[PDB]
Amino acid sequence: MTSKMSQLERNIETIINTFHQYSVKLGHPDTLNQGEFKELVRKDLQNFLKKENKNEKVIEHIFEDLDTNADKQLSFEEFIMLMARLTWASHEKMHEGDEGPGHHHKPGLGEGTP
Amino acid sequence: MTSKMSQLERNIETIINTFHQYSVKLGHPDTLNQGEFKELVRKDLQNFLKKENKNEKVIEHIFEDLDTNADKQLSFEEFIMLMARLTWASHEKMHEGDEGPGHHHKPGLGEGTP
Ligand SMILES: [Ca+2]
Ligand SMILES: [Ca+2]
Ligand SMILES: [Ca+2]
Ligand SMILES: [Ca+2]
């Protein structure tokens, strides 16, 4: 019974609100153009994107790549994908399957009689 | 100079660190099981998931659905799209009608007359 939300909850609202403010101003609220994408990362992550700032082409490359519709805009789902892609490419991996001892098995029933 | 990083930058580290701590403890660091998924949302979003807590099955349903590999775990990319799905699933709007669940069988004398 807690009336105070965790720090994580606050962050969720902050992320949604921040994108909404920039997005609503320009283009559809649920989509981001190249200008908004660059602006959001530059102001929020100027230190992390210092190298990105030097290469303008590098920055537009990722945005366009993430846009599957080639509509020069990214969907909400597409936007979060971009962040994940930046952190790690995540190459496709395959596994044969799951296996293990299986903890043997339960005992059978004697089914004996008096 | 940049001086200090914005809240958005801090939030990014917080999200990654939080998932990492729970994930590394149980299962692979880059994957989340049902227990971690439920635990992360419950502690961070106990107020938002109050209705979710009541229905345990509803909660496991979302996790399993998001898992395309049916490997009982979600990738980093899969995890972030789960949140997006929760926010908006394009659910149909509710409307008053005589529709309802079907049960038993109709009278033999009666006919479907399609
Ligand atoms: Ca926009
Ligand atoms: Ca698109
Ligand atoms: Ca894990
Ligand atoms: Ca999976």
Image: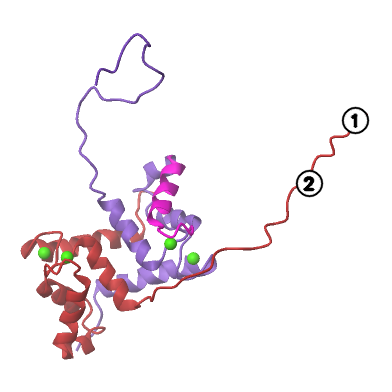
Chain colours: A red, B purple
- Residue B101 position in % (x across, y down): 34, 26
**Residue at left offset 13%, top offset 76%:** A39
* On-image quarter of the C terminus of chain B: top left
**Along the horizontal axis of the image, is A51 left or right of B51?**
left
- On what subunit does the disc labeled 1 rest? A
How far apart, in angstroms, are the residues tagged by discs 1 and 2? 18 Å
Quadrant for residue B67, please give it.
bottom left
Q: Which mark is residue B63?
A: none
**Residue at left offset 85%, top offset 39%:** A110
Task: Please tell me whether mark 1 sits on a helix, a strand or a loop.
Answer: loop
* Figure quarter occupied by ligand 2: bottom left
- Residue A111 position in % (x across, y down): 84, 35
Q: Amino acid at mark 2?
A: Pro
Task: Please tell me whether mark 2 sits on a helix, a strand or a loop.
Answer: loop
**Residue at left offset 50%, top offset 55%:** B35
Is the residue marked by circle 2 packed among few (<14), some (14-19), or many (20+) residues within 10 Å?
few
Q: Amino acid at mark 1?
A: Thr
- Which residue is label 1 attached to? A113
- Residue A52 position in % (x across, y down): 20, 86
Q: Is residue A29 magenta?
A: no
Q: Is residue A5 visible?
A: yes
**Along the horizontal axis of the image, is A24 left or right of B64?**
left
Nearest the camera: B98 or A16? B98
Instruction: Find the magenta span and give its range.
Output: B55-72
**Residue at left offset 74%, top offset 48%:** A106
**Along the horizontal axis of the image, is B114 left or right of B55?**
left
Q: Which mark is residue A107?
A: 2
Nearest the camera: B65 or B8? B65
